[PDB]
Length: 48
Length: 48
Image 1 (spheres, one colour):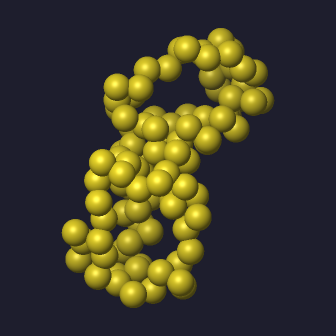
Image 2 (cartoon, rainbow over the protein chains, first blue to last red):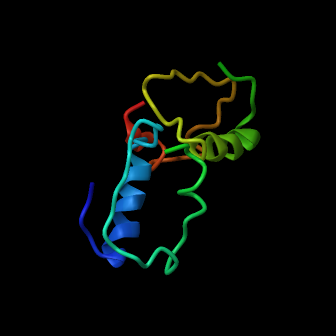
């Protein structure tokens, strides 16, 4: 479970994606509601 | 282990990373020789 701004999010979303931490066991809970200001599609097909 | 050229490689290196599989659980070995010609540092930053 996490705590960041959506500006800071897609940064560290990229950092989560670059580390190969995209296994389905990894569960993710965030704060920001702005789930549309940037991209979701490379973050979409990992199964998490 | 993977029968591929470097052309088809980064295509499926993208699509395999798009599956959320970028893990040193796995091992990867490739037929092609052009790896200095295709330099992928954000790919190699999962420690695989």
